[PDB]
Amino acid sequence: GSTSTA
């Protein structure tokens, strides 16, 4: 799993 925001 991965989650990234910007």
Image: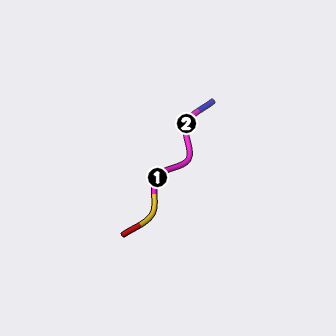
Question: Local crowd at mark 1 within 10 Å, few (<14), some, or many (≥20)?
Answer: few
Q: Amino acid at mark 1?
A: Ser
Question: Local crowd at mark 2 within 10 Å, few (<14), some, or many (≥20)?
Answer: few
**Residue at figure coordinates x 36%, y 69% from the top left:** 6
Between residue 5 and residue 2, name the one nearer to us. 5
Q: Magenta stretch: dominant SS?
A: loop
Residue 5 on the magenta segment: no
Residue 4 shown left or right of residue 6 in the figure? right
Q: Position of residue 3 (x, y in %)?
A: 56, 47
Question: To which residue does mark 2 refer?
Answer: 2
Write the start and end of the magenta stretch as one range.
2-4
Cα distance in 3D space between marks 2 and 1: 7 Å
**Residue at figure coordinates x 45%, y 63% from the top left:** 5
**Residue at figure coordinates x 46%, y 52% from the top left:** 4
Tell me if residue 5 comes above or below residue 3 in the rendering.
below
Between residue 6 and residue 2, name the one nearer to us. 6
Residue at the far right in the pictured view: 1
Q: Quadrant of the N terminus?
A: top right
Tell me if residue 6 comes above or below residue 4 in the rendering.
below
Residue at the far left in the pictured view: 6
User: Considering the numbered disc 2 on the image, is that residue within a helix, a strand or a loop?
Assistant: loop
Between residue 3 and residue 6, name the one nearer to us. 6
Question: To which residue does mark 1 refer?
Answer: 4
